[PDB]
Length: 433
Ligand SMILES: Cc1cc2nc3c(=O)[nH]c(=O)nc-3n(C[C@H](O)[C@H](O)[C@H](O)COP(=O)(O)OP(=O)(O)OC[C@H]3O[C@@H](n4cnc5c(N)ncnc54)[C@H](O)[C@@H]3O)c2cc1C
Ligand SMILES: CCCCCCCCCCCCCCCC[N+](C)(C)C
Ligand SMILES: CCCCCCCCCCCCCCCC[N+](C)(C)C
Ligand SMILES: CCCCCCCCCCCCCCCC[N+](C)(C)C
Image (tube, rainbow, N blue to C red; front, side):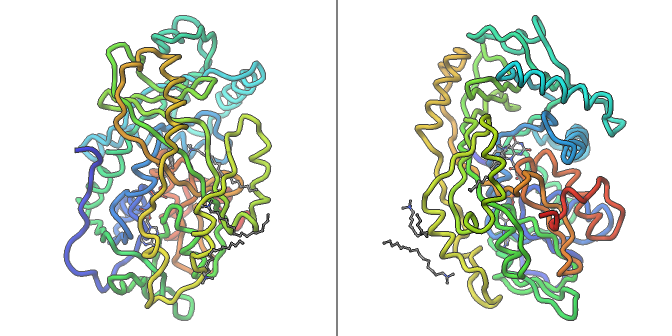
């Protein structure tokens, strides 16, 4: 049709659940799956529709490229587990092993790229083979078919993944449901009841579910959920426009990242996803409190963050920091995000793409949207225990949640159940700030 939809679990809201997941995005869905495999019966509550936010509004690349030591193995294994996903689910998630070329900006960028590849080749940290190398000549020109500029050198992540926003998370939701995961849609989680340390209930607009174990995977809303429970989660909003164009017989295929803001990725159906580099950070109330911690990100001149003043500031001041569980929460008050794509920005970006790859000159515009992130000061995920509430774990605050989800899921479940974590959880801890 155009977008793809998964229907929620029908009937009455259950009295009891072994574990309740807040949010039916990728992180919530994958964590649910991981828990079921361990033998737990899970219930996901979702304020809107399944994968209505970030998890159907992403660019679509699963890459380990330029990733720091903190997140590399989370991405490296994410790629590996996504390669087994189609076989595991038995339905096409649209995950493809695609390949990605990034032409560096400066000679200095080329040295930084070379060093990063060389450092990671000598010490991989996994028995999964590392498949990223610098490419020149014929190998590069085959990857850039019908390019105007004579590009000489690029970093080639051969095993870079591709997933499509209109399909990926939705298939994973249906697979979750087939495992016995119950997902209740249009059903916002306001907060939780706690008695003598142990969680007793999760309170929703449809009623209360008795549980002692909670997974918070509310995407951009995770901070606001933990605010009402008096736990500080440091995230700031970020926005990026995305667009989707039709295919071409003379189109180059694969994933391409070029100087001059040229970024495109071929989908499973032959259509092309493209976007500008520019990330828009709107001014919120939180900007005045801990926005100073985000200043070293504005340091890089290759960094594309614009500070913007819009309606988010006004919305921020009129979102409550505290609410009673028997009254209307901001998750109901601001249920559906209404953020629009920057249409002049997307147009200029597309015109640059058409100038570099004239194969796209005849391509028709399929879809244009805005995508909202929430990012921590060091740009790394929050996958953590919550000291203040035993049995509560949080899986959120990531710009790479699709790639990271199969490993994030296991790591979240490990923290919840007291098992030794898959990877070092210290860089993903809530208390690192
Ligand atoms: C423009 C853009 C491009 C991106 N490109 C890429 C990419 O190329 N590669 C990549 O790996 N990643 C990419 N990402 C990131 C990826 O989309 C996210 O990191 C991932 O979807 C995070 O999943 P999530 O479940 O935490 O958040 P979401 O998918 O937003 O899920 C959170 C859900 O929780 C629900 N919720 C919140 N509060 C409550 C409540 N109180 N009660 C009930 N439900 C609640 C929300 O309605 C929402 O559906 C991109 C993101 C954006 C915005
Ligand atoms: C320069 C320092 C001024 C201190 C005031 C800080 C508090 C903010 C007061 C509200 C200002 C209104 C901003 C409205 C922006 C929304 N729109 C862009 C959509 C109009
Ligand atoms: C001359 C410039 C005046 C600009 C002032 C406009 C500010 C209006 C913004 C709305 C303020 C939010 C309302 C507070 C209620 C929310 N809380 C209950 C959470 C405090
Ligand atoms: C002075 C106030 C500073 C506030 C700036 C806040 C910065 C917002 C953080 C955005 C940077 C994260 C970039 C990740 C984007 C990656 N993806 C495009 C893949 C999602």
